[PDB]
Amino acid sequence: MWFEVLPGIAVMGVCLFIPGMATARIHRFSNGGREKRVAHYSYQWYLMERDRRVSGVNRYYVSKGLENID
Amino acid sequence: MSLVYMNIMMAFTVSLTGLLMYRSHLMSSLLCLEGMMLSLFILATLMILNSHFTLASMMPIILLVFAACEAALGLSLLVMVSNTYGTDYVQNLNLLQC
Amino acid sequence: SRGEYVVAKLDDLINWARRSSLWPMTFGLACCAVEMMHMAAPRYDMDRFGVVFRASPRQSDVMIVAGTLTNKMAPALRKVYDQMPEPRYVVSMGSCANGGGYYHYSYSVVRGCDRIVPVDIYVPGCPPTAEALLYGILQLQKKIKREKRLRIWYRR
Amino acid sequence: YPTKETAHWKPPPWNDVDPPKSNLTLNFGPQHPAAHGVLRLVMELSG
Amino acid sequence: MNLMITLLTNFTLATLLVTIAFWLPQLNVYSEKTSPRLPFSMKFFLVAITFLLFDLEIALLLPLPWASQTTNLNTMLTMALLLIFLLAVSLAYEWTQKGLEWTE
Amino acid sequence: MFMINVLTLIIPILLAVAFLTLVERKVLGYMQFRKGPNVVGPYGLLQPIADAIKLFIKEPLRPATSSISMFILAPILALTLALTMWIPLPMPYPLINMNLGVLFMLAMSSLAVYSILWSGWASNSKYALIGALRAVAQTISYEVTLAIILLSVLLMNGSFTLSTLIITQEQVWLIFPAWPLAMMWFISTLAETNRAPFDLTEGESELVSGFNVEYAAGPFALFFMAEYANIIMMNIFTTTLFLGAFHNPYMPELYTINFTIKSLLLSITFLWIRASYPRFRYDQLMHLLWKNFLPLTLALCMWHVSLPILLSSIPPQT
Amino acid sequence: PFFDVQKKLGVDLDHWMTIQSAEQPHRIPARCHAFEKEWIECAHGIGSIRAEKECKIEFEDFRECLLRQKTMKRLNAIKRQRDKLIKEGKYTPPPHHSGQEDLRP
Amino acid sequence: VAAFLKNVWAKEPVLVASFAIAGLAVILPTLSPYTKYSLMINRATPYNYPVPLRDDGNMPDVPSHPQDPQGPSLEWLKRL
Amino acid sequence: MMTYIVFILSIIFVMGFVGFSSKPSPIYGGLGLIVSGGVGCGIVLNFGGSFLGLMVFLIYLGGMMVVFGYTTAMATEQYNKVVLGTFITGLLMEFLMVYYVLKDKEVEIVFKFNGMGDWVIYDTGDSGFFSEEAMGIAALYSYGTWLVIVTGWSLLIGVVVIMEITRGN
Ligand SMILES: CCCCCCCCCCCCCCCCCC(=O)OC[C@H](COP(=O)([O-])OCC[N+](C)(C)C)OC(=O)CCCCCCCCCCCCCCCCC
Ligand SMILES: CCCCCCCCCCCCCCCCCC(=O)OC[C@H](COP(=O)(O)OCCN)OC(=O)CCCCCCCCCCCCCCCCC
Ligand SMILES: CCCCCCCCCCCCCCCCCC(=O)OC[C@H](COP(=O)(O)OCCN)OC(=O)CCCCCCCCCCCCCCCCC
Ligand SMILES: CCCCCCCCCCCCCCCCCC(=O)OC[C@H](COP(=O)(O)OCCN)OC(=O)CCCCCCCCCCCCCCCCC
Ligand SMILES: CCCCCCCCCCCCCCCCCC(=O)OC[C@H](COP(=O)(O)OCCN)OC(=O)CCCCCCCCCCCCCCCCC
Ligand SMILES: CCCCCCCCCCC1=C(C)C(=O)C(OC)=C(OC)C1=O
Ligand code: SF4
């Protein structure tokens, strides 16, 4: 009956689920297990480039805490 | 001065000499006029963003709005000419020689 | 050998795709239009076979000639047939499209549409029932299923 | 002053109005030929 | 950069789909088929010009979600309501002088 | 690694467009008291595949074109714009996180009428060009209310950023403060994609869709799949815009499941509108825009300008 | 026919977009704010004739701030001489001009 | 005026809702008690840097530390 | 190469202007102006004019060139030496200018021009939590009061003027 449309809706739903889940997992893989840094404003980019310069490995997502100071 | 300003001014002069040398169509003339406007838009925008001159960021928008209303006026003139003569040819606009 | 196997499976693929996605153009000329419209009605439902109802005539696969072809609409019939992209098939529905029918001896009726277009399936009736037309559509699908376009291409 | 170049020039009309110097015909048919399919209509459209 | 990579990828996939959809049905050799100004409407041009002028008025309206953040809010609200009112007055003059007729 | 993310955007777009044809034919089947396809696959699941393979080996129709270049560029532009409308969509994370994703989508959708215009130029028939100009005038008409409704809603968002629009709707769906904007938005996006009851090209009220007319047209599958990419995209954009879901930043899959279910319901609502109403006449949807939607859209635009000021609810820029 | 209605009525119709050194939204400075302020405060009140020949240094500094012609010409000279010395092999680039020194902050 | 209003609400209710929503949008911010707070919140949002003052000796209202009592306060915004 | 991205987009911009300004047909001239508007938008976007570039796409290409192609479709008919000759003329003039300003890092047609990449002239600071371009455009409503008045009056008058001159009476 009407539940015969549910396989097509389910396949289309999996096909819509793949892009968002994909970009979330790729953003967590490319950024040290965390969210991708959002730099809409030039202050955010400034702090992000400062992180890239203080991390020592040319990667903004390598966070340096109090273990880096004396 | 900067290298991109040469190309944007040369784009203005290319669309100028296109606009100053008609072939047949009045529509191509209006296309050259709005290409002149486009090059003026880009040139003003590159100056104002380069200078960090904050208040003139609204200047290219006012340029775009006024010259697109001007373009609408020109298209309506072309439409009245085309409803008179059947085409948009500039050689049909020769009644005022006498 | 290997190439015969490959062109056989590719024939199977393209024949499956072409028979399972038939898009009909219907010349609903006369009473057989009513019975094709019943073949698209919810009981028989051509659309569950992949056979969409009210397909575009520009991109249709089968021309269902459903009604009396007169002498005055024979060139329009041939013009719509000539505007069809290949592979095009023609199902002749009903007695007047098959052989003139009840108007066989008329001064104004083409005695069967096969004087005008090549016909693949002849569906008999006045009208044939919507079930009989769906039988003819499935026989057309079986006719497409045993086509050998790439096998004959390979053996030439 | 008449010349060879300005020889064909006539003066403009007195009211400065020049003479002007049609409507579409459509051969129409029903979109999907399921219901009717056998209709021919020669329209005269004015837009 | 990633935007340019994405635009190039979308353009490439689109061009690949178009090239396939034109050249893949040319594989099967088919039977070579051998058998065998537009009228102007003023209303069609007028709806396009009315679009263009209201689109310029929209181009004026687009910096409003940034304009609400100002410290001159009374002037800002006055000019915002004034631009939307002039768009409405352009629509009213387009209405009452038979401009929106037969494409209403 | 980024190209993997681009491809896992754009290939499931094409697969979802493929199975939207199945979902359309099934749901329109059961609403019409019949079934949709169930023979070609189990429950019809091979119908998009069979239909695509059929369309890709079908002959180019009969005729030749007036302009080869625009006949090529109109499906290229249609598919390119239909794929680039998805890259700022925050689901929960956009592929291209930009500050102006709303204005990007509005501009790229404004560019989509050139495919219709160039396919009207590229056909040889002077009647197909008239039908294309009617379609262009329809789409540019409803882009006006798209722009103004979108601006009025973004006055509660604070920016053109699409990802901020998840943060804006954390306490309530944005359909609650803006349901008249939401319903005129939904009907205007319906009239954007040439979707019934606004589909005048694919139906009657048309001077050229009239059975045994001329006009060499493009390969139908490309414009068709561009159109269904636009349908799913505008429903996802309406879902983000008015029915924004819960987002846990540690579990993005909850937001992805929730916006996916809402976008499926909204696309089925498109399917359920096209199987419920007759078509507008052309001047009737011009009436519906210019005399009905645009006055309410300007009035609600004045309302949504002046309303955060009088309620002290001006959203932040950042 | 410069009918100075703005100075007559005291209204400010367009003096705000006129120069870069004016009041800006959120006090954003122009990149040549000081040079333009120096040229304007030099040339104020003395007229165009005295301003072209008595405020020439401030206007030259401001034009060279805007266009940066002397700066780009100087960098062209340095870069061309650097590339000539690299091609002749008589110069090596330092590690801090090659990306090998773990930048400051 | 009551016959005309019911007549235009029977014949053209879209335009009546249009003019009603527009008229409320015009006359309502001058009547609302929270329109003051919009200005107060926009002028309290610190985009720039609070560039400090040289302590000449007589500035009793200016604090010396951010946590000092004197200076502009946002307790009205925390509470509302 | 990649530091010269704004320059390469400006070369594509001038090539597109030589394309449509040589005037093959208003259809192809419209197409050339569309491609030129897109690449000049990319030039604006690569300085940080994101809103102004989206104004190019949304307003210029989105409304106005759509109306140009629309009106062309109502005034031309669907189905040379001078166009292709003037095309290659402008292309050779542009590439000779490119070659001079690249081999010399200097040229003077009307003004003196640098030959390096235009990355050199940028600022080295930030704008904080705003775009300076966005805030300057947002000040149209608080500082551009007279500018809004004359722009809205010109657009209302423009609607009136188009309804007058297309009326025919
Ligand atoms: C986002 C998820 C979905 C959102 C909801 C949408 C789902 C439902 C869809 C249903 C199917 C629709 C298919 C297409 C229909 C198109 C036809 C149509 O509806 O035309 C619209 C019709 C058109 O009118 P008409 O043609 O029916 O009526 C005749 C019109 N005249 C008189 C001009 C000839 O109505 C509208 O335009 C209404 C638009 C939205 C109205 C919003 C109302 C706001 C009310 C505010 C308060 C008012 C009270 C007074 C003021 C008080 C102030 C305090
Ligand atoms: C070297 C070896 C390889 C050589 C080249 C071949 C490559 C692989 C091509 C696909 C497989 C080849 C065979 C295709 C089917 C042949 C068998 C067949 O037709 O079986 C019939 C059966 C249904 O029976 P039917 O006759 O329809 O009966 C009516 C219902 N009682 O039909 C069914 O049960 C369903 C048939 C489904 C067909 C396969 C699935 C579709 C094709 C998928 C791959 C191609 C498309 C990829 C995606 C394109 C874009 C969407
Ligand atoms: C993100 C999710 C996307 C999902 C996309 C796909 C959705 C639908 C999923 C598949 C549903 C079931 C399909 C079953 C098809 C029919 C299979 C079959 O057995 O067909 C019979 C046919 C002939 O077999 P025969 O040897 O004649 O048998 C006689 C028995 N005495 O045998 C044949 O024709 C040969 C075998 C053909 C098998 C075809 C199977 C389907 C292929 C579809 C292409 C895509 C595959 C998935 C890709 C994405 C996921 C990895
Ligand atoms: C018929 C011809 C072929 C037709 C098919 C193909 C063309 C049509 C479809 C493609 C349209 C391309 C549109 C791309 C630009 C869109 C605007 C844009 O860049 O917005 C994104 C973003 C703005 O957001 P924001 O966060 O403020 O900026 C980043 C700073 N944090 O800004 C950024 O992220 C800036 C990124 C750098 C700048 C990107 C420039 C792109 C390349 C130049 C334009 C290319 C298109 C030219 C042709 C257009 C159509 C004719
Ligand atoms: C003051 C605040 C700011 C106001 C300005 C902002 C307005 C925002 C809305 C924008 C509207 C744009 C279009 C306006 C066009 C007005 C003219 C008009 O439509 O007149 C024609 C109409 C009869 O319609 P007809 O021509 O027949 O349409 C074809 C179908 N029959 O005629 C009518 O139906 C009569 C129209 C006039 C009477 C309407 C009365 C509405 C009253 C609502 C409550 C009061 C609201 C406050 C405003 C004062 C209203 C008097
Ligand atoms: C890449 C995948 C391609 C799938 C192509 C499916 C095309 C749609 C099939 C049915 C159909 C529908 C729903 C349809 O709406 C339509 O327009 C009226 C058709 O054309 C006549 C159709 O044939
Ligand atoms: S075969 Fe008979 S019933 Fe059928 S259309 Fe002809 S006359 Fe009518």
Image (cartoon, coloured by chain):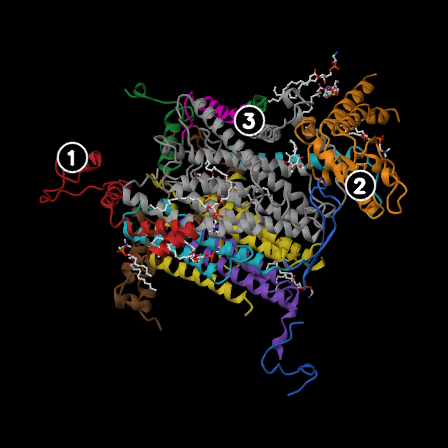
Chain colours: A green, B purple, C orange, D blue, E cyan, G brown, H red, I yellow
User: Which residue occupies the foreground of this view, E27 or E98?
Assistant: E98
Residue at disc 2, secondary structure: helix
Expressed as whole percent of the image width and height from the top left, the position of residue B81 reads: 60, 67
- The stretch of residues the image draws in magenta is A12-37
Foreground disc of the pair 3, 2: 2
A25 falls in the magenta region: yes
The residue that disc 3 covers is F8
Q: Quadrant of residue D5?
A: bottom right
Q: Quadrant of the C terminus of chain F?
A: top left
Amino acid type, label 3: Thr
Above/below status of F63 relative to B59: above
Amino acid type, label 1: His
Q: Residue furthest bottom?
A: D1
Residue in the picture at 49% in, 31% down: F95
Foreground disc of the pair 1, 3: 3
Subunit bearing disc 2: C
Above/below status of C56 relative to I78: above
Amino acid type, label 2: Tyr
Q: Quadrant of residue F155?
A: top left
Q: Residue furthest right?
A: C105
Gap in angstroms between the C-alphas marked 2 and 1: 90 Å
Expressed as whole percent of the image width and height from the top left, the position of residue F23 reads: 59, 28
- Indicate which disc residue H65 carries: 1
User: Which residue occupies the foreground of this view, G5 or C9?
Assistant: C9
Gap in angstroms between the C-alphas marked 1 and 3: 53 Å
Gap in angstroms between the C-alphas marked 3 and 2: 43 Å
Query: Could you tell whether B12 is left or right of I80 in the image?
Result: left
Q: Residues within 10 Å of mark 1 (few under 14, many from 20)?
A: few
Subunit bearing disc 3: F
Expressed as whole percent of the image width and height from the top left, the position of residue H73 reads: 17, 38
The residue that disc 2 covers is C81
